[PDB]
Amino acid sequence: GFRSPCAPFC
């Protein structure tokens, strides 16, 4: 998966 600490807006 792709869980970035700015998702889903960065």
Image (cartoon, rainbow, N blue to C red):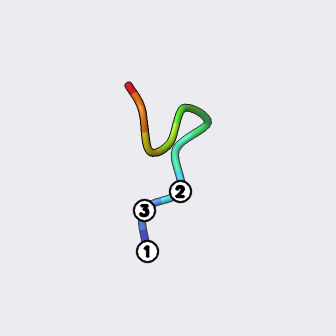
The residue wearing badge 2 is: 3
Q: Outermost residue toward the bottom? A: 1
Count neighbours of disc 2 (C-alpha within 10 A) and say few if under 14, some if 14 to 19, many if 20 or more: few
Q: CB of mark 1 within 8 Å of CB of mark 3?
A: yes
Per the image, label 3 sits on a secondary structure element best described as: loop
Q: Residue most toward the top?
A: 10
Amino acid beneath label 2 = Arg
> Left or right: 9 with respect to 6?
left
Q: In the rendered view, does 5 fall on the left or right side of 4?
A: right
Q: Are marks 3 and 2 in contact (CB under 8 Å)?
A: yes
Where, by quadrant of the figure, is residue 1 drawn?
bottom left
Question: What residue appears at the point 38 percent right and 25 percent down from the top-left corner?
Answer: 10
Residue 2: numbered disc? 3
Which secondary structure, mark 1? loop
**Residue 9: image x %, image y %?**
42, 32
Q: Are marks 1 and 2 in contact (CB under 8 Å)?
A: yes
User: Looking at the rendered structure, which numbered label has been put on residue 1?
Assistant: 1
The kind of residue on which mark 3 rests is Phe
What is the CA distance from the residue labelled 3 to the residue labelled 2? 4 Å
**Residue name at image x 50 percent, y 42 percent:** 7
Q: Amino acid at mark 1?
A: Gly
Res 5 → quadrant: top right
Measure the alpha-carbon separation of dots 1 and 2. Answer: 6 Å
